[PDB]
Amino acid sequence: MPGTIKENIIFGVSYDEYRYRSVIKA
Image 1 (tube, rainbow, N blue to C red):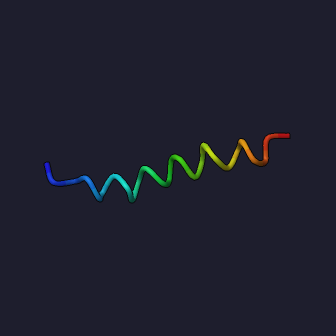
Image 2: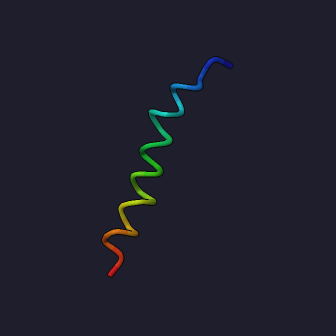
């Protein structure tokens, strides 16, 4: 399935959520 890029469009919605709670952790 040619969805490699489609992931970069969701993978960010997840990472941005994993790297956002860390920097703002407490």
